Image 1 (tube, helix red, strand yellow):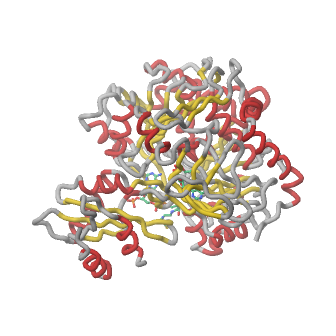
Image 2: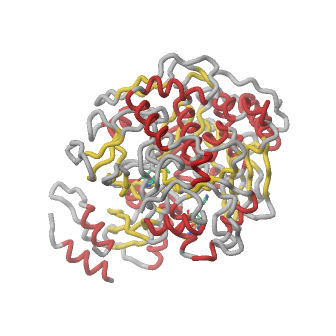
Image 3: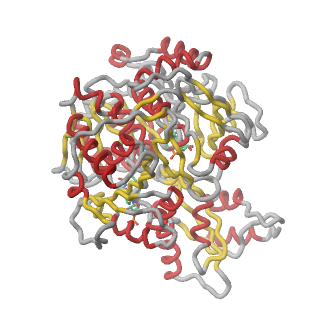
Length: 633
Ligand SMILES: CC(C)(COP(=O)(O)OP(=O)(O)OC[C@H]1O[C@@H](n2cnc3c(N)ncnc32)[C@H](O)[C@@H]1OP(=O)(O)O)[C@@H](O)C(=O)NCCC(=O)NCCS
Ligand SMILES: CCCOP(=O)(O)OC[C@H]1O[C@@H](n2cnc3c(N)ncnc32)[C@H](O)[C@@H]1O
């Protein structure tokens, strides 16, 4: 079953099937003309001359786009929209409590970004300084990210659900000079500590770089205050001049770092530059969502994740959209919350995640009860695979069978959408990301690196660069080259597996490395094992993912205690809380399986394939039998 392109979409679409085909072929055959022309979606301070300048050569990866052009992201997201659209809403903010919302016009946002840019400059922040942002889903998170970009500071946004230890690791690695936070965030009626977590983070004796903490009063909770270091947001911004002249950034000036979990090691800072990234986010946002002036757009992703960077803030604002920032969760106070927000603000484009869809579907019709949903023209899904059944529930209940669903496959490392439908150009298959975006050349290779032709499956690689590609890993270009460009030479390895069907549509099966997907959150099995083994009573651990109906994968941890320690309710609780402390609640094992029987190769390497199979139900060979009975209990 292919879903046809509906007439209302065909009548209005920016790109039809023929235009998709033609532009696709040109992006591939002639990237310099294609991306040379498409780069004009942005305003450049000085024009680029060179367009594509890239190599995936082994141990010698170099990615540059538009390299001689200069520009300012904040000017593209704000300034250039003032003359025509200064009165238009830039951001609709919907509170965790429905009595709370705000409309923030382009003019108002610009003025606050200008005030906050001066605040930053007056505080001593300079172009290239890294600024850590640990904020909830409030408009001020946006102001802080845009102010940083405006001055050429390099923001590093840390998701609010990270623990103080996780916050400190990111601060240490990036040498962040400043932390921007709130006293607390508000989520599903609960107040979540943020500033306290920062206080704990800065007590780590390896944190040396942070000179100030800017705190937004979001809840007025009693916090500890260090005079001098700590500064209230309101105090600072109100003293700052609202006049700020944006300076030109080179196309290859660093824009942001985003810590991202890998197959091995601890999270690394995926680094995006300015020009290609922003051309790519604005271009993909515009065509995949079929954005028309006046469309109300809603991405539900947190600002702490890449989806929140590219498609909550940067892509939409570049295009002059009204973008909605929701503080809470789609099913609080009730499962109908998400659709209530859609009606309240007349959302035309809704972009969400399969975990949220599956949580709402588990509530059947309570998800749509009392709601109208008519304003909706376009639906999106990203972050994890969506089965045909969930896709169909989404298409029917939320979109009322009237809205194309754009299932967008991509990654932190890709900056923007990679394999995705375009709503007026491509016919949909439930559960398929479908076809590559402009400038994207995917392939499927076997474990030896041989391309597989026709209907097939294999390792999903991208065989050439695209403007939005991550340029490096902060402080570690060698690890960037190793992780992504060493498995299959001269190719970008995504670490995902995929099938290609008889039509040439891609079906992403999931990570083939040791990376988990837990409620749409990318986590490394290695880092969770490191966190566990750091516990004074734990000798060894092996972490796998198991299928879970809502979350996609749940975390299953095999744990070996040091001699002289026993399993108890207490130790169970302590070990789970230890992971919460090391990483955050998102990384907490759902199951602890206590064992002295980790399977290992003769060289001592833990073999996870079998652990994966046992946990799901599907040197010393005796360990498998012990493991089987332990699992059954
Ligand atoms: C958002 C949604 C997609 C799934 O939620 P989720 O991302 O998996 O996270 P949850 O809401 O379950 O919370 C898990 C933990 O992470 C924390 N967390 C999640 N987001 C956070 C954030 N933005 N900032 C700080 N902490 C956060 C929660 O507080 C909770 O921690 P705790 O139990 O130790 O106090 C959607 O299904 C939803 O609204 N969840 C309902 C709550 C729930 O029970 N979810 C589990 C599946 S039903
Ligand atoms: C939304 C982008 C999130 O970026 P992150 O870097 O956090 O996660 C990237 C990984 O999410 C999965 N993934 C993402 N989108 C899809 C998708 N649409 N279908 C299947 N899997 C997906 C793929 O496994 C991918 O390697």
